Length: 107
Ligand SMILES: COc1cc(C(F)(F)C(=O)N2CCCC[C@H]2C(=O)O[C@@H](CCCc2ccccc2)CCCc2cccnc2)cc(OC)c1OC
Image 1 (cartoon, rainbow, N blue to C red):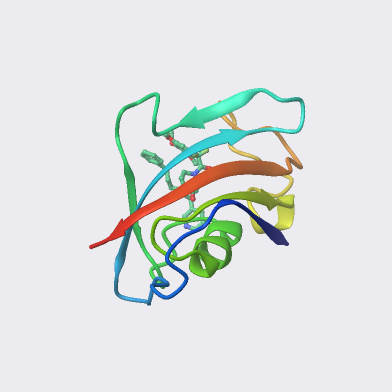
Image 2: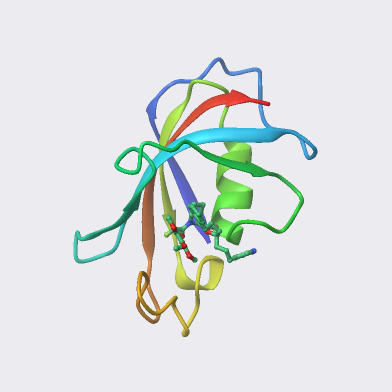
């Protein structure tokens, strides 16, 4: 599944609701410690809407547990990410993913 470990606290009262757009910055790393992506490196905050099946399960459920301003480490098992397939070119087969995520604001 997905384990959420807080790095820095959010406001503790503003959690994402389906229908809201979450705006975040993240760095994604594999088990071997290699970075597979960073919105910070691309200088482009990642935005997604809960309940629209637009992100992996680990994100859908993990980012949901975060309050605005929170920074947390999400550790996602392959069944909650890309499974056996992975995503050739960025994520290998059966990969456990670790995302350092910061919930900036809700739009
Ligand atoms: C799957 O392909 C990508 C995955 C990432 C990723 F590794 F960071 C990643 O794994 N995610 C992106 C940030 C949110 C969490 C996760 C993700 O959900 O990506 C989805 C979409 C984001 C891809 C993207 C990210 C940033 C810029 C453009 C596109 C994958 C779409 C497939 C899917 C899975 C489950 C349900 N519905 C759809 C970054 C990418 O580009 C920067 C990707 O496309 C080139």
